[PDB]
Amino acid sequence: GSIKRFRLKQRLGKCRRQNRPVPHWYRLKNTKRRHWRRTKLGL
Amino acid sequence: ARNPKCPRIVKSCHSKTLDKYGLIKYPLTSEKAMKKIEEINTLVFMCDKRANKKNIKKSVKNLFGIECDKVNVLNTLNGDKKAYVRLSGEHDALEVANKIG
Amino acid sequence: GKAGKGTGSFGKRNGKTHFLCLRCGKRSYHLQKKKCASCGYPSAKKRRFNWSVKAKRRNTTGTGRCRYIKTLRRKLKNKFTEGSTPKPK
Amino acid sequence: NVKAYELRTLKKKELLDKLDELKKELSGLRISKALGNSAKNSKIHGVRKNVARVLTVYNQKRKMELRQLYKNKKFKPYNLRKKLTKNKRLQLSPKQKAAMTLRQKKKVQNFPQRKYLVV
RNA sequence: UUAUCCAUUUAUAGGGAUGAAUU
RNA sequence: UUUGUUUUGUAGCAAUAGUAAUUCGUAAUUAUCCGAAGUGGUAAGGACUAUCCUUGAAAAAAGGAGGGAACGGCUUUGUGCUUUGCUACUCUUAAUACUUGUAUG
RNA sequence: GAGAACUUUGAAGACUGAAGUGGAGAAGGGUUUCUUGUCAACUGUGAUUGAACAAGAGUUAGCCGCUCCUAAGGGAUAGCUGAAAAGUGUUUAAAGGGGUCCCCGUCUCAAAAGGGAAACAGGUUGAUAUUCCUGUGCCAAUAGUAUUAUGAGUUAGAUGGUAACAUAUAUAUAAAUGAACUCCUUUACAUAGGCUUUACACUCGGGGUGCGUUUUCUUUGCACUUUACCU
RNA sequence: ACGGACCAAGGAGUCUAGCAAAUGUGCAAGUGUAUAUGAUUCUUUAAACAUUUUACGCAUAAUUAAUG
RNA sequence: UAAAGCUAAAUAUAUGUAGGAGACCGAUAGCAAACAAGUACCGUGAGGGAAAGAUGAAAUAGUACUCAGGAAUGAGCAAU
RNA sequence: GAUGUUAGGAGGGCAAAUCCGCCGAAUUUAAGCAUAUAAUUAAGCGGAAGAAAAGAAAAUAACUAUGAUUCCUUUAGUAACGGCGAGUGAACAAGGACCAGCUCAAACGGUUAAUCCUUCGUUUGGUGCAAACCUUUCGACGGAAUUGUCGUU
Ligand SMILES: [Mg+2]
Ligand SMILES: [Mg+2]
Ligand SMILES: [Mg+2]
Ligand SMILES: [Mg+2]
Ligand SMILES: [Mg+2]
Ligand SMILES: [Mg+2]
Ligand SMILES: [Mg+2]
Ligand SMILES: [Mg+2]
Ligand SMILES: [Mg+2]
Ligand SMILES: [Mg+2]
Ligand SMILES: [Mg+2]
Ligand SMILES: [Mg+2]
Ligand SMILES: [Mg+2]
Ligand SMILES: [Mg+2]
Ligand SMILES: [Mg+2]
Ligand SMILES: [Mg+2]
Ligand SMILES: [Mg+2]
Ligand SMILES: [Mg+2]
Ligand SMILES: [Mg+2]
Ligand SMILES: [Mg+2]
Ligand SMILES: [Mg+2]
Ligand SMILES: [Mg+2]
Ligand SMILES: [Mg+2]
Ligand SMILES: [Mg+2]
Ligand SMILES: [Mg+2]
Ligand SMILES: [Mg+2]
Ligand SMILES: [Mg+2]
Ligand SMILES: [Mg+2]
Ligand SMILES: [Mg+2]
Ligand SMILES: [Mg+2]
Ligand SMILES: [Mg+2]
Ligand SMILES: [Mg+2]
Ligand SMILES: [Mg+2]
Ligand SMILES: [Mg+2]
Ligand SMILES: [Mg+2]
Ligand SMILES: [Mg+2]
Ligand SMILES: [Zn+2]
């Protein structure tokens, strides 16, 4: 909830970062997305 | 009491421990930070996750003509520390903002 | 019983038995017991079993970069003395 | 953009000074990036590389100095020692392995395995 | 009794005739 | 220094803040903010009384007491101790200065 | 807006009805918060909405917690078992602290509801606030040496009060000698029952302000009339 | 009685060991060059070739619990 | 000639790395995995564990332009 | 004997196909099942190496005798074991691959431990661009050791 350990917080942040979509410019030279409600991080 | 004939491990390399450049990464824009700069002479800096308040203060002293009364910090969910730095009354954050950029 | 064995009882499922595990990063550190289910974390030993071949394969030496081991491979082939560069120019 | 061959000749203080300047420059670039700019965003990479180069040069100089300091003297720091697979380090030196009990040595000296061409 | 075993304690004076208590 | 009378103070915080108004301007002024009481819902405290073959945690931390160890400072002489001579001393907070790693969170 | 029963605003009519779809938190979730966009899919009807999609942003503490203490307990040290793995935790230990050699003495984790240094009000953001701002405090540190001041005491350690006990009001009650070694107390405690005291809530009547009713009636009905920690 | 809604693809007497019979083939009181060696053998060659300038198997004799 | 000890070779290798081969498999096959595969995802957990290859010679030919559409798309006398 | 953050070092964990120790089942087979079988297997625990282990006869033979170990061909599905059921089952010889032997202890040397190690050194060399290595013999100052080091066989 609203009191995390630092490690957990960092993990959450990491997950969030992972979430974001392919930078579109790359496509000129993703399947692991997760929606917070349907698939859990299972931490 | 130790008296080793030679020391075990001698890191001859330049220190890896974070200097001013590396500790404090960049100021924040964003409307919030701009507002802060305007109204209550608080400069917002993104910093390394392993910056302390003391350390941040030191960095600020070194990197700019800044004297800081108080520094609040927080760990952002992007893996950066955001340090809210309230300047002493002698300085105008706006002027210092201008100086930095 | 509204909190009966099925759905009602799944409502009372909060509170982790396992958390993250320093060492394995695998959310299988039994908090109350203070022991990782896939490591034996406090035991200085990895807790792997010949009866779990799949398990064995999914955490062996090859699986994950080998920061040092990889670097040392080829050295035998080269057989260069340590400390030695090539000739300049 | 400073490449290493220029930097080897420089003294350590000078190198340090250079490095600090480079770091400052990098910081400036970062600040610019943070602010709404993309003018010299691509300049940063080069600066970073330069910094790295400088660090490398300085580090090697330091290592050399250390080596000079600890030349011979039986024991040394474990850094400056022969970093080498643990087993090899443990292993008996070839000479040690060779070393023969005196009688055996004598025997070897007297009756060595001869060459003898059969016809 | 000395092996062995059990107990007891800070291993605290060898055997007999409703205060304080320390340098 | 104690008695009598009066004027203040929402005791300080405190009206500068809030609230409800009223205007005036393209943020400022003004006026208000106070005299009686009941109900006993909630909480806390108090003093008690009762029940138990149920008598209802511990420690960090703090305090108090008992006890009487130790005992001024400076100057001079001899091997921390003893002798000789003089009277501002022992505390105590607060500030200030200076070296000692940069002596506030 | 291309398009609206289910997007927005207003006007009605309703419901939740302080055991609330109201305010706060815990577990759990993890960015779902927020603004700007926005509609391929999803939002089992529609959809311009959205907890969807995209871009950015957002979480500020000496005082709120964790952090310290110990609890049921856990993991270990000594041993001792056991082929080991493990199993037991003073069972036959040479097991770090306190004073000026003596005297104590397993370690460590285990409470985000037990124990516990200290914070309140108002304001402010698109999104944070006992955390920022203004103001007002509080707590704990604060090394030595030297000056200053502040007061005590002595010309080596105050007095009062019959007593219960009281007294340092200096910016601020700071100071009333105290070692070893002891002994207490606080920490520190069940449930029930009523009784009482205070605050909060509610209400009543009066004064003051505004709004409401006004075919008729109503000195009227409603709102506001506030006051924190700290001393 | 059971299985079968439909369609596509996958989907079940195999491989080794040792024995036998059948049949083919070679040689025949022999037969099989077994390991291994050797070669002017070396993409194929992990095959093919060779057998030192009385090995062993099965057969050639049976029978007995056995000395035989 | 027990109750002490050492010792190369011929031997083994379904592990790892690197080579090389095949009367082997050819994307429901072959490793679970030809692809960001021990990945996603499920399970408190020990564990479980997928699907998913092919445009063309060349996208340095990946759909310009016009019309109708709110747009998707559609159409073309237009186009690679 | 404790004690040391004394000086110097070592162990710990990962990985396992082959390998070495333990520990150790049952499904299964026997048309049931109980000994047997599965199997001195799987799992478990520990430990090594490029291989490991074994190994230089307290061996086999009964010959005209061989001569460490290992491995292959065989002996041999034989001797033997076995509710003599199911089933299990070697060894020697023979032919090869490969072939390597040894040192402690004990005996002997006291007109003398000749040994051994730590630290500090000293000065000829060799390859290297350096870094490092490679060897060379010479003392000291320590210790260890007569409860036994070294040589001799
Ligand atoms: Mg949580
Ligand atoms: Mg859910
Ligand atoms: Mg904070
Ligand atoms: Mg539990
Ligand atoms: Mg006011
Ligand atoms: Mg709906
Ligand atoms: Mg209603
Ligand atoms: Mg109702
Ligand atoms: Mg939202
Ligand atoms: Mg729908
Ligand atoms: Mg929106
Ligand atoms: Mg989203
Ligand atoms: Mg607190
Ligand atoms: Mg503690
Ligand atoms: Mg306990
Ligand atoms: Mg235990
Ligand atoms: Mg604790
Ligand atoms: Mg608590
Ligand atoms: Mg909010
Ligand atoms: Mg039927
Ligand atoms: Mg049937
Ligand atoms: Mg049917
Ligand atoms: Mg069917
Ligand atoms: Mg035939
Ligand atoms: Mg022997
Ligand atoms: Mg051996
Ligand atoms: Mg496949
Ligand atoms: Mg190990
Ligand atoms: Mg059976
Ligand atoms: Mg059967
Ligand atoms: Mg049966
Ligand atoms: Mg096993
Ligand atoms: Mg060996
Ligand atoms: Mg054999
Ligand atoms: Mg036969
Ligand atoms: Mg058997
Ligand atoms: Zn683990």
Image (cartoon, coloured by chain):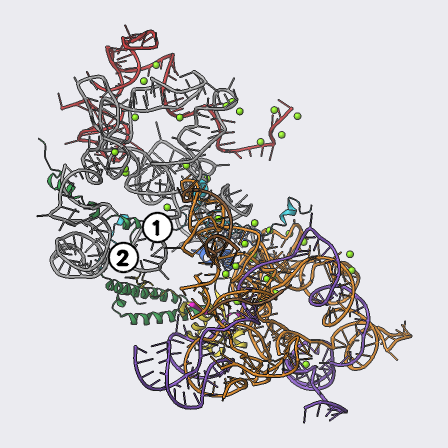
Chain colours: A blue, B yellow, C cyan, D green, E brown, F purple, G orange, H red
Please name the residue shown 60% across and 50% down the image. Answer: C13
Q: Which residue is mark 2?
A: D81
Q: Using residue G21 as the reference point, say whether residue B42 is left or right of it.
A: left
Q: Amino acid at mark 2?
A: Arg
Determine the chain carrying the residue at label 1.
Answer: C
| Percent of width and height locating residue H23 | 36, 13
Residue labelled 2 has its Cβ within 8 Å of some atom of ligand 28: no
Q: Quadrant of the N terminus of chain D?
A: bottom left
Secondary structure of residue under mark 1: helix
Q: How far across and down, in percent of the image, does residue B80 sit?
A: 48, 64
Q: Give residue C70's mark.
A: 1
Q: CA distance from mark 2 to mark 1?
A: 22 Å
- Amino acid bearing label 1: Lys
**Closer to us: G48 or H17:** H17
Question: Position of G217 compared to A38: left or right?
Answer: right
As displayed, is residue B62 above or below residue B50?
below
Taking the image in four quarters, ligand 5 sits in the one at bottom right
Placement of the C terminus of chain D among the 4 image quadrants: top left
**Residue at mark 2 shares a chain with residue at mark 1:** no
At 24% from the left edge and 64% from the top edge, which residue is drawn? D69
